[PDB]
Amino acid sequence: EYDYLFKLLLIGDSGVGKSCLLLRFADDTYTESYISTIGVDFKIRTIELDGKTIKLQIWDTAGQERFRTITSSYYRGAHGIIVVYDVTDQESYANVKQWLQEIDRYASENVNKLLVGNKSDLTTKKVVDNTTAKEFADSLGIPFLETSNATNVEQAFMTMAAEIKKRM
Amino acid sequence: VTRIENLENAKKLWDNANSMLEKGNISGYLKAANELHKFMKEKNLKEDDLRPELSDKTISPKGYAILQSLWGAASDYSRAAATLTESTVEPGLVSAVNKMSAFFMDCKLSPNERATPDPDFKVGKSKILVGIMQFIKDVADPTSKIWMHNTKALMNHKIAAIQKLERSNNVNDETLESVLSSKGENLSEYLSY
Image (cartoon, rainbow over all chains, first blue to last red; front, top):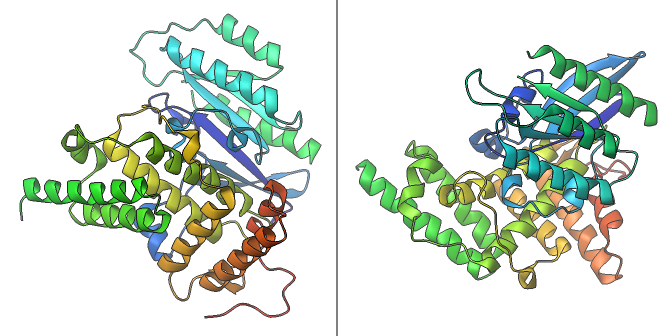
């Protein structure tokens, strides 16, 4: 049982390295026949803050790359939204910018968000200026994180969980 | 049998699913997508194995609209179903449906190819939700439970709830969300069968 359950939405195309952000989450454990054949699109973990037990449940929602119109599936029903672009890929940044502009338009101010610039591999070429992404992030008033180093990803989740807890 | 034969059978299965999609048959699409998934798991075939065989197949704008309708409803339902009462079985089941539908799409499409849905063929959210639940009721283990209730039985209970909202003209995202998030906490007896 938990004091809180915080729902996180992980938004990102294929090939931007979303797996990288999910290493401190685990799959739930099933006997259910139908689930055991296919799996699920969310992962879980438990943390403790201020004496309170909090489940974090993160959805990397199956099929999301196919439906990129911004609907209430993207802007409602999550405590936190994590949007991931690939630093080696200008069109990736351009798409996420757009998605986040639209999410900003329709979401509650009460939803925590995070822009993540990921770079999966040591050896591809960087092309997205972090000043520009940071300038964009500041404009919507949301944190920005550049990731490769697993450490700062954990800090980001922890800060987001802390901020969600203050508003709930 | 050979890999070439198994691929041809998988192709036929994918086409069956695509035919149901075109007919707007929600139950029949979901069953066919499941039969595709089963057969490809049995035969150790993955989406990238089938994809080059489907090169001249197409998912229609109507098809995409149905897939979109399913996606939105499942996305929303998996999240709403995650509560402090329970957050494992009902989100799991709903998420597993959604993945099965992504699987069908992944057999045809390369990574990041966007759907091109025709809004004319959008299915109402409350009808999609009943379809998903009916499929869950079919594939759930007989002894499966969501919290203290039999899964099949809660699926029937939520179905009735959505149908009653329809009848009193009180379907909206908030009323739907309130059924989707319920675990029957206020029921005097636990649901069986």
